[PDB]
Amino acid sequence: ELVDNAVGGDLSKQMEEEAVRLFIEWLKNGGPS
Amino acid sequence: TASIAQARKLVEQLKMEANIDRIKVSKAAADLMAYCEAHAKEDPLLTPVPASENPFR
Amino acid sequence: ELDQLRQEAEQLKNQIRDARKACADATLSQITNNIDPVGRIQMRTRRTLRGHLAKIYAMHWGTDSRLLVSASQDGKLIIWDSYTTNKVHAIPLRSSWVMTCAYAPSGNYVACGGLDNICSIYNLKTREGNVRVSRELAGHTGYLSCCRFLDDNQIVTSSGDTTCALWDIETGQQTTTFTGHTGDVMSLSLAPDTRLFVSGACDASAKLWDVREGMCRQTFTGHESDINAICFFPNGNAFATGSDDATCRLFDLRADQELMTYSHDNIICGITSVSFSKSGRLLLAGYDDFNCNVWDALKADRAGVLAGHDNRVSCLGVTDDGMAVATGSWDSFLKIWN
Amino acid sequence: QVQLQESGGGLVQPGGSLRLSCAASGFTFSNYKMNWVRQAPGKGLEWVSDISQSGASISYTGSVKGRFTISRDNAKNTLYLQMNSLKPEDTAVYYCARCPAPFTRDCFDVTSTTYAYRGQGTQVTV
Amino acid sequence: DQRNEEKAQREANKKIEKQLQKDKQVYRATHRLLLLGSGIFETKFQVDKVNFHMFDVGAQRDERRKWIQCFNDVTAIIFVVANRLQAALKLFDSIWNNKWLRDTSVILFLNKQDIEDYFPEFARYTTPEDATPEPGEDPRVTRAKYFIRDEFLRISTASGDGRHYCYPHFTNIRRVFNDCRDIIQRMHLRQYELL
Amino acid sequence: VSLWETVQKWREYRRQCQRSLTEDPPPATDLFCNRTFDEYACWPDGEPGSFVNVSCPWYLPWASSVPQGHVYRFCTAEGLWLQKDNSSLPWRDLSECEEPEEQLLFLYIIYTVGYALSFSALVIASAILLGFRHLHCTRNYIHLNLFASFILRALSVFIKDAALKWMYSTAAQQHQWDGLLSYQDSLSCRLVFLLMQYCVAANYYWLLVEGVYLYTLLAFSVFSEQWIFRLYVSIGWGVPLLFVVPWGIVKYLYEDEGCWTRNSNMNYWLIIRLPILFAIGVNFLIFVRVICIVVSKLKADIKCRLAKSTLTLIPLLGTHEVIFAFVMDEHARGTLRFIKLFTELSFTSFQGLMVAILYCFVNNEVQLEFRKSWERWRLE
């Protein structure tokens, strides 16, 4: 049981969800800027 | 008789050693002082030696 | 018979003491107070010879000063090359325990003494092959504490059953025997003219021995305990002795009694070896609290402390030209100091 | 010059209070654990008692328990032995002795082949 | 000239270093033992492929203080005994309280099972009932045997501090083998500071 | 949810929209607000004066939860839409289809602080061991390699943290999608994570190597020193690489999907996971044997000595790792997981600090060397 790997996966997933939301916001607000 | 024999040898040794002359302490101490003063020039521990002459560097 | 003989010995010893006291006019400190002191010079480790496994019990320099011999307890006798830190010859030992080593003034012979009561002589040249035992001197019945060479052919050995002996190599028998002490003869040193050798034993007695005659001319009794190691002043008129009461004493040959005593209250450990510098103004003493205090020989001051080692120092040697001091301790390291 | 002298001894009525005194000359007295060793005639040397560097640690042989008192004074630098209620089979020469090193606890002085620092002894006859 | 001598010195130094490595391997394989009850007699044996060189002093003068100091490097001292008992006790105390023998464990053997006259503390003695007496014997022999063992233990416990230990045994090679293994394991635990 | 998938879906949606733009006929002859695509929603022909509807676009992650919405705009009479402001684009209707932080933050903070503190303590400890040169021994070689392995693990987690933090949020707020995609294609992602897995496996196997070495010394007591030391060093560095390399080949060939952090298929990750469990089991077995031997020697007061010995022994061998890996796993299904995760993370992060602390303070030889050298330094 690799504890660091488990923490890393959860942190990465939360960060990825935030990144996708930011990308959608960027597309709506400006397109390709 | 071994004990008394060794004790006799001890007495004979004491008799032989008692006879010899003894110089005064001041003269011999002066000799050691003079020897130290004479050889104080060439002493690598007393007088420090730089890295040039040093083989151990 | 014992009572009257004992009375005669008591009377004669009293006469010798009274005679020495009458000959005593001053201390060395009184006249020599007016000399400049050394100050302090601390030394730096320059080489570290790490090849041994067990504890290094004895080391002996060579007259060349290029090469030193060290003997451990693992049965290895190693002839180091002190300048370029290499092992010239490593020799296997028949017996594990070796309490002394001696290196010849020609650099062709190496003598090692152990508990096995057999002094061994190793030839170094050996055009046929390896270094090998050539002739072994087996006459003592105690153990062999120290040994030294007079030349390449005759070797003086200090046994542990009270009898110092002078040995011939090509015959193999004792030429003469010295029977003065009542104790284990710990260490002997040789005068620079190689005619007289002092003997240190466990009955707190220092004696002056004549090589050709075979008799003890003088007796020096100034210690409270056994004498570990003894060293001549480098001309041949005095010598220093190290004991287990934390006193180094300087003994005079011709005034026949102690000039000075090197003991401070903070030192409660036994001396294992004493040596002098080149001129003789510095007295080197290995101590049992893991360092090598340096003594001002005319002023009785501690010039400096050689505190590199980690265990009991067993042997201490100074080169003939006086360039360096190599100490050997029980942590299997030879440290060379400048 | 180190020598231990002993004053006392001699004939005693069995049971008599005989005292043995050892006088030490030639060394600092206050540093050495000094002991008494007795030689019975026709017998090897046997340790009797010892007292430490201060005067606190005192030990005895089993056969001499409760009859011998050992006391040391530093100023008069004397090793003093007090013997009480003597016995004829325990008659012997009594040697004052010194353990060979300062400031230590161990001793190696039972040796009959001329230990270097014991005294010459006094005959003690009961 | 210079290149040749330096290269040759490198080869000679490396050959000597390899010989020292072989000697180091065989030296660490060897467990030296000292037996005290030609100036020295060597007895070599091996029990379960572990090499034990046992050395017994030969013609050595009876004063012991100087030469014993060399023997601090040993793994264990086998001490065998048999007013002789009091002299043996004084000797064991001297070995135990030495300034240099504080690291050596003493293995004790009680040969010639016994007397009663020399010890007026023996009359007040009771058998250690934590210990198991070996059957088919004499209660007086068992009482005296444990009494001597207790005297050695009381001498041992004075400033022991775990630097070195004393093992008491009765009369032989397997016992020494087990005790040496015990000493080595205690030494290794001391290195890791578990104990 | 995947950024990679979302970008590919958006680009395909944009292409399909362009196709619609290409093939749609001209509107009603010839005044009309012009057909358009505002990079989110693809619009058809706009009649002047009408709200015109298309589906909420399929490339959104949460589009299927709101299919009943549309987007709407209004075209005014001038041939231009309901702009409502001159500089900006026309009106838009995104309202129809728009749609634990503290716990993970706190965990991130505590493990990063634990690794930093452990990194500093181990660096100081390594320097202390190397500098004295009198403590140089075979067990000290094993300790030096263990400390180095912990340093490698700390560096790997810091590099993974920096690369991952730069990857998603920082680059997007600096608006670097071309660079973000370039790193996504880059093999630096395909190697940093391999390095991180190798460092973790190296740490666990080095813990095993020290345990086996201790058991070897106590049990066997006879060996050949050069071969045994080379074997321990080879096993400790070599075998984690031996397990990691097939996992890397399997991941790279079979999946290679985005960055490898997702860990989608459990079966592929079983290959790396199982040797760590085997190392943990062997280390626990060795621990039981050593505790048995220590108790036997101590019996041959007792509770206090045993407590001190076991407490010292646990950081250097990972008994806490053993219990968390097997007993506290609970089939990996327990709720209030946070407490378990928090405790395990704290123990793992502080293990390096604890092992360094024992040698720095408790160890008598280190303390004696420090006193001796300090006294010499002060004197001269």
Image (cartoon, grey):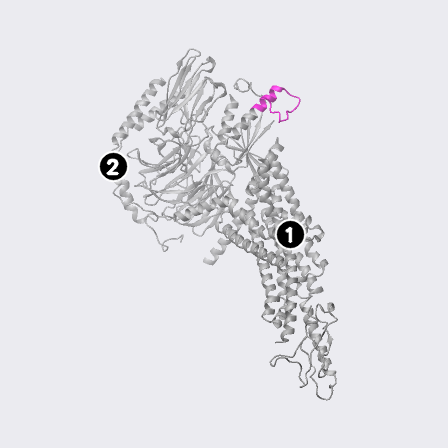
Residue located farthest toward the top when viewing the structure as drawn: D13
- The image's mark for residue B26 is 2
Mark 1 belongs to chain? F
Vertical comparison of F197 with F327: above or below: below
Residue kind at label 1, given as amino acid type: Ile
Q: Which residues are magenta?
A: E126-147
Asked if residue F241 can be seen in this view, the reply is no
Vertical comparison of D97 with E26: above or below: above
Mark 2 belongs to chain? B
Look at 53% across and 23% down and name the residue there.
Answer: E85
- The image's mark for residue F222 is none
Q: Label 1: how many residues lie within 10 Å, few (<14), some (14-19) or many (20+)?
A: few
> Residue D96, located in which quarter of the rendered image?
top left
Viewer-closest of F259 and C78: F259
Look at 51% across and 29% down and name the residue there.
Answer: E92
Vertical comparison of F267 with C181: above or below: below
- The image's mark for residue F339 is 1
Residue F40: give x, y in percent of width and height. Answer: 68, 75
Q: Label 2: how many residues lie within 10 Å, few (<14), some (14-19) or many (20+)?
A: some
Q: Which is closer to the viewer, label 1 or label 2?
A: 1
Left or right of F246? Residue C308 is left
Pick the quarter of the image with the N terminus of chain C.
top left
Q: Of helix, strand and loop, which one carries label 2?
A: helix
Q: Of helix, strand and loop, which one carries label 1?
A: helix
Looking at the image, do the residues carrying marks 1 and 2 touch, with CB atoms under 8 Å apart?
no
